[PDB]
Length: 131
Length: 131
Ligand SMILES: Cc1sc(-c2ccncc2)c(C2=CCC(C)(C)CC2)c1[C@H](OC(C)(C)C)C(=O)O
Ligand SMILES: Cc1sc(-c2ccncc2)c(C2=CCC(C)(C)CC2)c1[C@H](OC(C)(C)C)C(=O)O
Ligand SMILES: [Mg+2]
Ligand SMILES: [Mg+2]
Image (cartoon, rainbow over all chains, first blue to last red; front, side, top):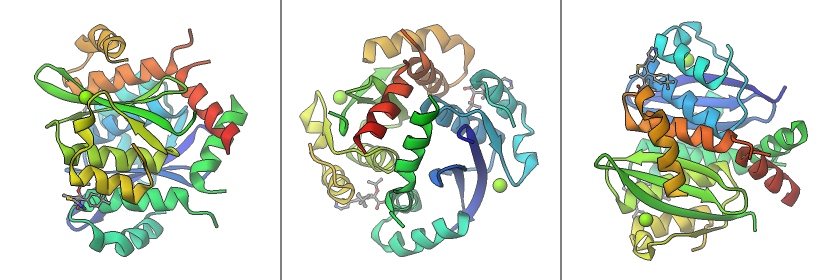
């Protein structure tokens, strides 16, 4: 179902990576964040929701969505309630970039553009059809 | 044509807002950035390119794309070379949020979800068709 996303944080090099997966396509968005925090999560959701038709969000750690900041973002945006593969791609391009956040975005790109239709194409095809 | 984006910076409250417009749809992405810098622009493009099939980018200030960081990001991602309306929406929601970056993302959401088909729907429809 096309409005369903998964959201979790991983850790790498002492930093936090917020990973969102569009469950039906495998498409990912990610951001390096300073702190694993309610407010960072809330902001990330605001951004994600302005870009895609987000209806529901799941996570493997329910306490992620406990802050009032997160619930207020879900309320306003109308939202209700891969990490090893991405680390794999991060490891392969890690040498090419100084900043982890750069390596993360290179890895997101590679992941979404890989054909093995790509994830980036499936998300768009699934969403257009549903309209 | 569907791989064409426009990219510029505006200023608000002493901060920098990087605004990307998908020319064929009116769809926008935006980010508040600390500094109007080559490296911020480069990073923004990396992110944008991992999410949408970006072919070409235009800007109203050509010197924006002069840094080696920007050219290296365009090279790696395979890329070649609204602000008053968004400020309008920012002004309307500005009171609801503490941080400008939050007001910016609320305004991007509103702009992409408005029907007056919405911009968010047109981008997806235009891209799916082209595949
Ligand atoms: C801090 C720098 S300098 C620099 C650069 C400058 C000139 N030529 C090549 C790379 C780069 C790039 C490396 C990989 C890239 C393909 C994303 C493009 C730009 C970066 C890069 O940071 C950016 C993306 C500019 C914030 C990095 O973390 O190393
Ligand atoms: C720094 C805070 S606290 C807070 C909040 C907390 C509890 N209830 C309502 C709003 C909010 C929210 C305001 C508007 C919103 C619709 C995006 C949702 C979350 C914020 C918000 O910053 C975030 C989005 C958390 C980084 C802000 O700039 O004011
Ligand atoms: Mg988690
Ligand atoms: Mg400009």
